[PDB]
Image (cartoon, rainbow over all chains, first blue to last red; front, side, top):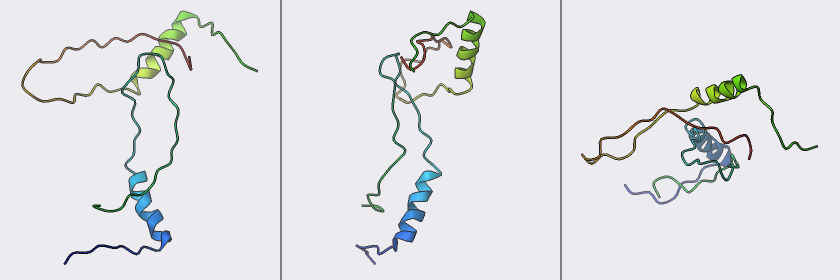
Length: 50
Length: 50
């Protein structure tokens, strides 16, 4: 088979959005004093395997 | 209000330097068989929020 659409009541888009939540772990690698960072803590969904 | 200075008996600069070490980990990213890496384990303090 070869699917193209997923239908997903948005009670379950929020479950798929919660799997990424358990695996995010923000990390800072570029730091030499200047430009104190600033955070957002939000993200969107681009699909599953395209 | 808004502050401009911090005064810090330099024992506590060494404590503020010590709280960085429980929140850092050196990590390596490239793998090509050249330039065996060089370590330093030292880091300077640039203040707090600028």
